[PDB]
Image 1 (cartoon, rainbow, N blue to C red):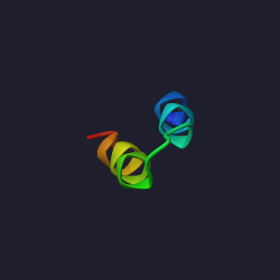
Image 2: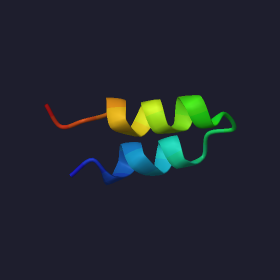
Image 3: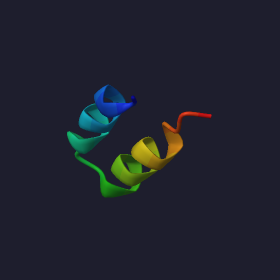
Image 4: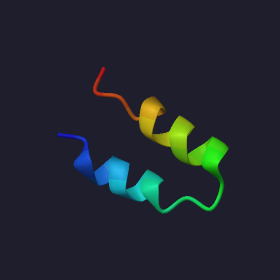
Length: 28
């Protein structure tokens, strides 16, 4: 589960970075 990464990306000041952070932090 990548719930941790998600939460970390949620607290992103920049949206472009927030979304990219989550979508980028996939399971692979």
